[PDB]
Image (cartoon, rainbow, N blue to C red; front, side, top):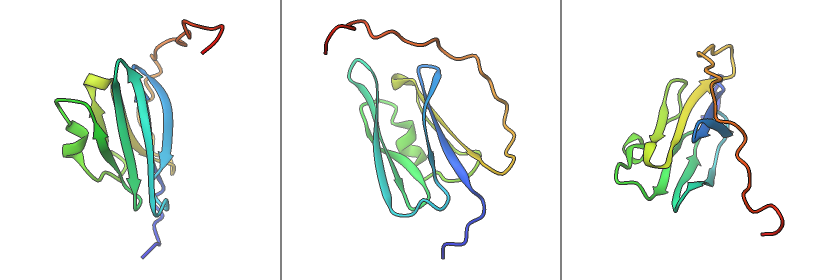
Length: 114
């Protein structure tokens, strides 16, 4: 029913930096969030019943759409046309290789008004 001890979280990174991470295990019900990156390039992600998938995105690959419901430590969601890379890791000592070679803080080229 709802006794799940394998507490895993989905790590969302884009362009080469971690932008968000959603807990899957125990996270019952439905949840949605839109990953906006470059020119018109976005990924509408959906977490429904302790599992995550790409609900909709504008890519000719649609790889994450083929991936479907992912929810275990080791599952991934990859949309290179949008530079979105997602991997699922567990909270309980799930020691994955932490490659920290990320992209520098991107400047908002319009800082003065919207």
